[PDB]
Amino acid sequence: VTYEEEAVPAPVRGRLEVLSDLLYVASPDRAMVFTRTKAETEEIAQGLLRLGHPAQALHGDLSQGERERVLGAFRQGEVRVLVATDVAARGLDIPQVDLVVHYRLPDRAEAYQHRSGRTGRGGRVVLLYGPRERRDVEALERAVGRRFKRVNPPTPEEVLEAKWRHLLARLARVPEKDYRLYQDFAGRLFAEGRVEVVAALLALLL
Amino acid sequence: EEVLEAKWRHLLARLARVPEKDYRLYQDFAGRLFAEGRVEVVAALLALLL
Image (cartoon, rainbow over all chains, first blue to last red; front, side):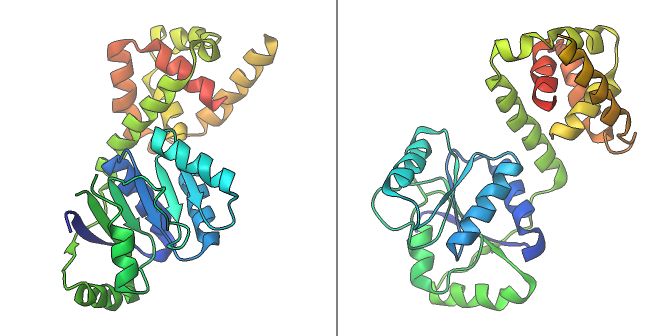
């Protein structure tokens, strides 16, 4: 064990947004989110993509090729979050990561180490848990013989500033050509002096 | 061409619908852009929204 362990309260209803928030504030080069079923990896991964993270599901129905591209885009940096089940996460082809998140709790201690050991190229392991899930976290803590520091979810201001920076990376990727046709409308908003409008755009894209 | 100035007018549509309370949090960010005259960023911006 070389990592920080945190258990973060997160109601199953708003788990996806808690997870996104965490990813933004942490800003890992590489994150791995574990979940129980392969169907969940693809709901989560799609969700995180909606919310602006470059996320990809890793699960057992992927063809070797599909796996090879996901894991390839992972190493390279093109993809930053992998949402995986325990079984699909098996193998020696997965690069070690900065952060591991337990989107759902591991059914046993072994699964907890197998999941958690993937971090620390030690990095940070975060467990999300629900209201009637705290008994479960306490068991893991006993199985594991270790106590997970209890930490609150990120604050909406920490989150907001992190979003803004992540957005500035995205924009920077837009090729000059793609945006030269608009540089005129921007010169208008700017010179014409309208802050409210620019803040209005951000309000959407953020 | 005119294909652009069109959605550019209907962009403002959904734009004026935003509350002076919901887009408040983002005035600082918008302010930073102005301070720096980051014209390309805003161009790159609405290019992504349209």
